Length: 129
Ligand SMILES: [Cl-]
Image (cartoon, rainbow, N blue to C red):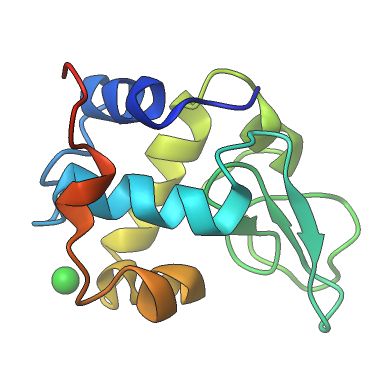
């Protein structure tokens, strides 16, 4: 599924991401935009042979099992294919574990390079939330 900006903001707000560990909704929408272009079906292969999955590009090296990342952890205890669903529940619940692991949203390279220190509330402007 390819989300609209406000559609995704509303879905993330309903799943409890607005101000989760102090990150306003704008931060999550901005990260999703640059990670996946709001496409739940986004996959990208890393140099290490790991693969990034879904709207928040969650990595198979640490977070999910794709059956092809040797020696990897499955710290969200899900198949990576669960992260490609039109329902963002699995992506959001895993993201909550990631952002809680000590480095906050710095875990998302596109958030650090394209969202951090910007006016992120611009991403939820005009939305009915
Ligand atoms: Cl933090």
